[PDB]
Every structure is written in structure tokens, then in C-alpha cells.
Image (tube, coloured by chain):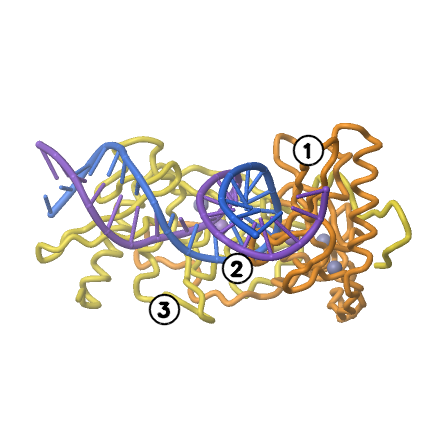
Chain colours: A yellow, B orange, C blue, D purple
Amino acid sequence: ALTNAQILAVIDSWEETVGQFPVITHHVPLGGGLQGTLHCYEIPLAAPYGVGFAKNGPTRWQYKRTINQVVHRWGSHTVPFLLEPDNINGKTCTASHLCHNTRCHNPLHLCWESLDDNKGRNWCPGPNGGCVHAVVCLRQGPLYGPGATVAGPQQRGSHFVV
Amino acid sequence: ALTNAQILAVIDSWEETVGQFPVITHHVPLGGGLQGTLHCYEIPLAAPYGVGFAKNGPTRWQYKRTINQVVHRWGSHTVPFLLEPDNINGKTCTASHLCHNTRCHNPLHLCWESLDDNKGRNWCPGPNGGCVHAVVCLRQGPLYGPGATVAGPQQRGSHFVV
DNA sequence: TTGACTCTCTTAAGAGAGTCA
DNA sequence: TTGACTCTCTTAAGAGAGTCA
Ligand SMILES: [Mn+2]
Ligand SMILES: [Mn+2]
Ligand SMILES: [Zn+2]
Ligand SMILES: [Zn+2]
Ligand SMILES: [Zn+2]
Ligand SMILES: [Zn+2]
């Protein structure tokens, strides 16, 4: 099995490579009518992506390193968390984008949590709008707001009470 | 079926049958430390479910009627909305449980909205905790809260900024 | 050892359609 | 005509593994 030193070396090589990705400045809602700035380190749209990186789906990538003649591969956003527990409350841990930018691989924009926790950030009011996430959101979720409901609760007769 | 009269007859038959489902009272968090009461009309756990109803999945049902000698079938929660547009902004409209209770078929607990709007209600703080849904939530979402994040944003080197 | 592709799978909110009696 | 089963599909947040040179 890979040693602690070996895993740290994988994380360090990943950081070195991702740090050279194009850095894009994005202005983002924080909640409470305030605006902030995030700096995303974005993987390229097409090959080549960077040393060790390859695309396995339209918005999915993997990182690969060969150690002692054994090929090791990980989801592209999971590498910062290789020394952390991989489950919690019986649920698999997932890489969660605090910046809501899939191509971004900035580890300061990622957290490690259940898929349910991950998804819910899409609707969070944000760090200046009432976020209660213990690991705080960096921005208001892109789907926060009144919504676009087409039809609300209703009945034609009198068979029901709320 | 095709006619408005036929569609109204389908909604009326569905309401009459669902109106005879057992009414189960559920006390629910509203947000803001307050509690409310919902009355769900719950489809039975096993056959028979009611005239026109059949189970197509562990928590999925369909409603079926014969009109002009042809069988017409719909997802069991979609019937109240048969006169509404079936899409919004190019996204499919879905039946969305304001009570977060799949077996419930009370139309006073359903709305018709995109899958994203639907999902997002799971994390809403609720009608007394800050819900901003234009079609208001009936309760705080079951997944609202601080989460259980295992690891937050972090780097080993000095290549990244927020 | 490495790059650039290929394929299918998970989850939890939701769907459509066919086989028998 | 009605009932009680069977199967796979959609979405958008996420995954693992194979092939070839
Ligand atoms: Mn996410
Ligand atoms: Mn729902
Ligand atoms: Zn980012
Ligand atoms: Zn948050
Ligand atoms: Zn209900
Ligand atoms: Zn709400």
C-alpha cells in the first residue's frame, strides 16, 4: 500500500500541476446583496490538460500516477483529501465545489462531504445571506431564490385539508 | 385524454379516490423553532392501492383510466397538473412534495416545478425560518442544517488563493 | 510510465412503458 | 376493463475501471 509519504508526494505533485492551470477571476454573489471575488484554477477544455490528468467524461477527469510499477488513479478533485476519512454517517465522501465551477481544481474551493451536503450548497443563501454550513460556503448557491414554480397546491373539490 | 372535459373528469376521479386514502397527521419543523401540522393522504403500502392506481417502483405509482376504449396512464402525482404546461424554461415540470412524504397524494401538498426547484426544497429553512420560494414551503426541508463535512478547503503548499 | 480516449456506475429527487391475469 | 406486477429511463451533483501505443 502507498505510504503516508507517498500519498503526500501525490498531493504535492497534483498541487504543483493544478497551480499552473489558468487562474480565472470571477465576481460572485455572497448573499445579503454583497458581491465577492473567487479565483478558480480551471482545467483546460481539451487535451492536453496537464501532467497526470485525463478526461473520463464531459465534466469528469482523473489523476494518475505510477509508483513502484503500479498504476494508481483517483477522481481529479479527490486528491486533496487522500489523507482524510472516505465516509461519514454511513455515507461516501465526495469532493464538493464551494465555487460551483466543475472545471476548477483549486483545493481552497473544495470540501469533502456527503453527496446530500454537496448538492444542498446549490440553494444556500451564502456566507453573507444566512449560510449555516459548519464548513462555510464561499458564495451564494447558483439556484438560490424564489424559483419558477408553474403551479402551486390546489384542489377542484373539497376532499382535502392541508 | 384529449378533451378538457375528459381531463377534468380524470382529475375529479383521482381526487375522489385519493380523498379516501388514510389521513395521517405529521408534525413538522417550520423553521424558527416553530412546529406545524400537515395532514397527508397516504397511498397504502401494498395492493390494493385504490381504483386506478398501481405501483411501478418501491416509491413510484401510476394512475390509469380507459377513455374512448384506450388506456391513458400518468405518474400518480402528476394528475392535478394535467392542464398546466409540462415544461418551464426548457426544463421538464415535475410533481414536487411540499410535505417531503412520497406516499402522500394530497394535492394541497404538491406543486409543479422544475426538478432543480423540487430538489432544492430539501434544504429550505422553511416558512418560519426564511423560505423565499414564491410558492411557499409547508415545512423546513429535512436536510436543512450545518451538514457533516469531513474536511474543508486546504492546501499543503503556497500555490493557491481563494 | 504516460496520454487520450473508451465504457459503465451512484444517489435521491423525479419519470415512461410492457407482461400477465 | 381493471389490477398487480415487471423492466428501464432522467437529471445534475458526484464516481471506478479498460484499451492501446
Ligand atoms: Mn457541488
Ligand atoms: Mn421533492
Ligand atoms: Zn473555483
Ligand atoms: Zn452554505
Ligand atoms: Zn403530504
Ligand atoms: Zn422554501
**Disc 1 residue crowd, few under 14, some 14–19, many 20+, Cα 10 Å:** few
| Horizontal side, residue A114 vs residue B160: left or right | right
Name the residue at 74% across, 52% down. Answer: B51
Name the residue at 66% across, 40% down. Answer: B73
Q: Nearer the viewer, residue C5 or A33?
A: C5
Residue B96: x and y, percent? 68, 49
Q: Can residue B41 be seen in this snapshot?
A: yes
Say which amino acid is labelled 1: Val
Which residue of the protein is positioned furthest toward the right in this rendering? A158
| Horizontal side, residue B36 vs residue A41: left or right | right
Q: Nearer the viewer, residue B117 or B38?
A: B38
Residue B93: x and y, percent? 66, 39
Same-chain status of marks 1 and 3: no
Say which amino acid is labelled 2: Asp
Residue occupied by mark 3: A85
- How much space separates mark 3 and mark 2, taking CA atoms? 16 Å
Residue occupied by mark 1: B70
Q: Quadrant of the N terminus of chain B?
A: top right
Name the subunit of mark 1: B
Name the residue at 20% across, 54% down. Answer: A72
Name the secondary structure under disc 1: strand
The image quadrant of residue B37 is bottom right
Residue A29: x and y, percent? 60, 44
Indicate which disc residue A117 carries: 2
**Disc 2 residue crowd, few under 14, some 14–19, many 20+, Cα 10 Å:** many
* Label 1 beta carbon less than 8 Å to ligand 2: no
Q: Nearer the viewer, residue A30 or B41?
A: B41
Name the secondary structure under disc 3: loop
